[PDB]
Length: 31
Image 1 (cartoon, one colour):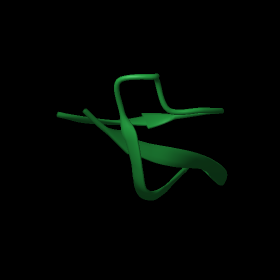
Image 2 (tube, helix red, strand yellow):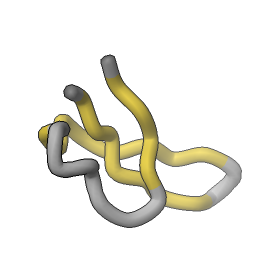
Image 3 (tube, one colour):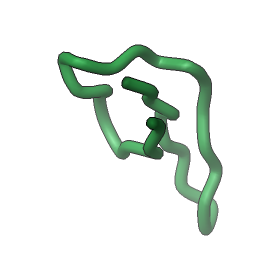
């Protein structure tokens, strides 16, 4: 399960990529 996060991935997640939403960049984090 994955989410776009504004700063860091949660401890239980790994960084899989990035998101771009409304001009703002996110880290894409998956459990």
